[PDB]
Image (cartoon, helix red, strand yellow):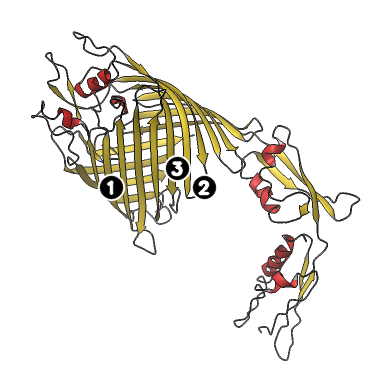
């Protein structure tokens, strides 16, 4: 029954200082257990470990009194010699690189052994994915004595992957993508990938190179070269056009706060447009760039450009979970700008926010909110390139409205012309959207699989306008004020989502609470996706 005191006995070398306090566990009745005496010993043999003494014998050998019924516990500490690390080396690394492994090393050479930063480095080596096997050695550098080399013996491993996805959704339709990837290319710890994918709207091929380092301090250098073939002809986010673009880009990533990060990028991009059936606001751009038109031609003599751009962003993530966060928030601040050598001459800036509030110790009843702000303008007597405009609608912006159904309408030519107001969304340079939802527990489902599904009731609301439409306002008194930010739409609905064993399904039934004439309403919306 119980214990008197604990004086921490043993040897040697001023260890009794940081050993004693305060892991001696002052007192509060001083209980004692059979299996709870194992780990306390380990706590001490680690304090020595970081200080140079790996080998350490901590012997719990308490002697009890059968009269006073008071166990006098005793720390019997054999602290061994102080182990000095000469140099660390690797073997089995046939393809890798002394570099690529000696980057995850924390322990320093010609320095006292710290068996933690050492033991934690073998853990850092694993979890990279580069090796199947990582194991360390302590051989003692004969003759010396008391010095050690610590070797890391790795088994290289297939760091090449191939991957496919297939998916279907209300807007987007049938989607698939494939990609091929070699990590640790080529023993340098970077990653090279080939990727391609298909929407109804585009096919996009993409070569990308990622250097996680570039600076010792973790700054990343991403390279990307890409081709996109966009074709918009099947929609309502008509004001259809065809765009073919190629480009290439380097972007610097900065890993600051685990919850925060920045990036800076430069990129060159070349866009080529065909079709483009010639409408009012677009013409303003076509002329802005002084390409020719010449009626009786409908459509434009094809349009081309590049486009050196600068890019900066900031990324905040709290979010207590990968998917279905239950608390925390997340946010982004991003900006694009075209540089002196570009055509086009414009800038973009954006901001999103998503946050989650639980009403519960439980976390089953959560209130979530989301808001986004997007704004483009141009300069140098140039208009914003019309294919760079915003629209809202659909999951992600305004449920119950079809994708890209919210924004300024096109006005095509009817010779005299530009008195053929259309339903087609041509898009705008200012977007705001926000959303508020109550996540409630999923009925019928549960209890073990109750995560994996998220039921909710929401209100979405969005608005897309053209800031410059004032210059064109009169001349079209019988069309709405396309420059009025107040022509906000909104909806309310139920929304189900679930992470099935085949991939993520998410559903939505939404009814509009505010629409405008000619708005395309798509109440039921859903996506379905799989990856292999």
Dot 1 or dot 3, earlier in sequence: 1
Q: Which mark is residue 435?
A: 1
Of 503 and 197, the residue lying toward us = 197
**Rendered image quadrant of residue 114:** bottom right
Dot 2 or dot 3, earlier in sequence: 2
Q: Position of residue 77 (x, y in %)?
A: 78, 70
CA distance for labels 2 and 3: 35 Å
Dot 1 or dot 2, earlier in sequence: 2
Residue at 32 percent of width and 19 percent of height: 242
Q: Which residue is mark 2?
A: 256
**Left or right: 515, with 198 as reference point:** left
Local secondary structure at mark 3: loop
CA distance for labels 1 and 2: 29 Å
Q: Which mark is residue 501?
A: 3
Q: Position of residue 166 (x, y in %)?
A: 42, 31
Q: Position of residue 289 (x, y in %)?
A: 30, 19
Image quarter in which the N terminus is found: bottom right
């Amino acid at each position: 029954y119980n214990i008197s005191e604990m004086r921490i006995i043993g040897d040697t070398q001023k260890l009794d200082n940081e050993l004693n306090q305060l892991l001696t566990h002052f007192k509060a009745g001083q209980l004692f257990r059979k299996t709870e005496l194992s780990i306390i010993e380990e706590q001490i043999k680690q304090i020595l470990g970081d200080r140079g003494y790996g080998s350490a014998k901590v012997d719990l050998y308490p002697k009890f009194n059968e009269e006073d019924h008071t166990v006098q516990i005793n720390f019997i500490v054999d602290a061994g010699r102080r182990i000095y690390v000469r140099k660390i080396r690797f073997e089995g690394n046939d393809v890798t690189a002394d570099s690529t492994l000696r980057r995850e090393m924390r322990q320093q050479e010609g320095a006292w052994l710290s068996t933690s930063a050492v033991s934690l480095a073998k853990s850092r080596l694993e979890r990279t994915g580069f090796y199947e096997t990582v194991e360390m050695s302590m051989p003692t550098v004969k003759n010396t004595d008391d010095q050690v080399d610590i070797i890391y013996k790795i088994k290289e491993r297939n760091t090449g992957s191939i991957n496919f996805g297939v998916g279907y959704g209300s807007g987007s339709g049938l989607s698939y993508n494939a990609g091929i990837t070699q990590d640790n290319f080529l023993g340098m710890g970077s990653s090279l990938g080939l990727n391609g994918s298909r929407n109804t709207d585009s096919t996009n091929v993409n070569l990308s190179y990622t250097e996680p380092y570039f600076t010792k301090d973790g700054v990343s250098l991403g390279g990307n070269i890409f081709y996109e073939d966009y074709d918009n002809s099947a929609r309502k986010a008509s004001a259809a056009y065809k765009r073919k673009t190629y480009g290439a880009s380097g972007t610097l990533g900065f890993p600051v706060d685990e919850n925060n990060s920045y990036y800076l990028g430069l990129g060159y991009t070349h866009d080529k447009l065909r079709n483009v059936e010639r409408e009012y606001t677009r013409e303003k751009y076509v002329n802005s760039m002084k390409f020719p038109i010449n009626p009786q031609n409908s459509h434009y003599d094809r349009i081309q450009s590049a486009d050196f751009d600068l890019s900066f962003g900031w990324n905040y993530n709290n979010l207590n979970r990968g998917y279905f966060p239950t608390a925390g928030s997340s946010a982004n601040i991003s900006g694009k700008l075209t540089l002196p050598g570009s055509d086009n001459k414009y800038y973009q800036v954006g901001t999103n926010f998503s946050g989650y509030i639980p009403l519960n110790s439980e976390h089953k009843w959560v209130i979530a909110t989301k808001g986004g702000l997007a704004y483009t303008n141009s300069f140098g007597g140039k208009e914003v390139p019309f294919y760079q405009l915003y629209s809202a609608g659909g999951m992600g912006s305004l449920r119950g409205f079809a994708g890209g159904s919210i924004g300024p309408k096109a006005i095509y030519y009817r010779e005299d012309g530009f008195k053929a107001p259309s339903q087609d969304v041509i898009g705008g340079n200012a977007m705001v959207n926000a959303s508020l939802e109550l996540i409630i527990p999923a009925p019928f489902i549960s209890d073990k699989y109750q995560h994996n599904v998220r039921t909710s009731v929401f209100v979405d609301a969005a608005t897309v306008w053209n800031t410059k439409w004032k210059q064109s306002k009169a001349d079209y008194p019988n069309l709405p004020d396309f420059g009025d930010y107040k022509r906000v739409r909104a909806s309310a609905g139920i929304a189900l989502q679930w992470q099935s064993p085949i991939g993520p399904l998410s559903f939505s039934y939404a009814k509009p609470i505010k629409k405008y004439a000619g708005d395309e309403i798509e109440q039921f919306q859903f996506t379905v996706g799989s990856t292999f």
